[PDB]
Image (cartoon, rainbow over all chains, first blue to last red; front, side, top):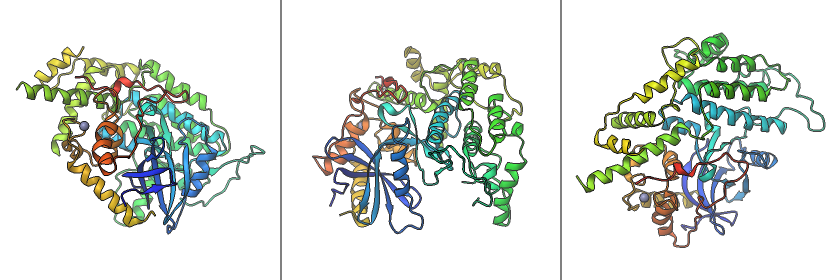
Length: 374
Length: 101
Ligand SMILES: [Zn+2]
């Protein structure tokens, strides 16, 4: 009754995620007690893919950030896939940080995503569905490692016996937000299209929005048309206005790639790694949500101290907590300026550090212990 | 067996014990903290990663005890903090999970 099991090894716990026409459940191994994620797909679905990506995970097994499948098989009405438990997605962490990421976090994330994508490409695969929702963090000591999920639209771009690329095709069926420009044109997706999609995600992280977002039209077909009209029209410079030039150089590189040529992954790595050096970012594995969760927890336990010896708020209180953390780690938090239509130099970006150092929060007696923290 | 009705009854009792059966003075585990987030993953999978006793995380010490262990006393969950730092994965500073008094 209350003991539902999958694959005779895992018990089903609380529901954690709801995929499209599917559900994701937290679970534990009956014998070892290891936490697992359980994906359930009903057989009565118009487009089943759980069996397919099950084969993909097992083929991409042995890679960093590639979720190791613990078991796949059928359970009653459902197809059941069991992997090791993962943390929230980047879209989840985006909402956690109120949809704005620091320059540091974006670069740290970009460097991890570059390796994930290159590995998948190195196994003769392309993802074809790159969005913040398909990148998850680990739990426990894997919490620093970015993982990749959802290979339902994944496809082999080359043969294995020979490295010959798939032929150039058109009128291939048109995720409108992060899709490549060539994907809108019906052109076959390639390795270039994945990296271009990745760029759209990174720019989306810095600005919190994209040009094709929030476009209005009377006829709903025109709504979809305006977005396509937007991607093709917008220049790379306009797209990466308030961002460092490294971002523009990335998008320019990816959109200039041929249909079959191999990307210079090492160049993309150095490009942002050089930027982090300029911005004086160190490899300390500290994301925005990492410092925010810590600062939040540090402040809230001080409440109990005050008591013993004594939804609108959330946007205001998080703002107070974000500012305090911004003061505690002034070198880490650098953000994109909405006003700027030019590419800011590392100096202007490093100028924010001084501003963050000379920052003042509302809380008085609580901040006194935050001074005592040091 | 595994049916849709079975999953419903299983999830109902869990969220019943999740709503008002988690009795601790922990701030993150508190019901007030869950109203703040509509995306339960940010709480259950990200904020329960924190450790109040620097031995077990909140998902093990608080959640597993009040939600799972109450439904079934034999329901097992491991301490993922006791696990190794695996070679392939990026380094995880455990200091980010430790709550300062
Ligand atoms: Zn608690």
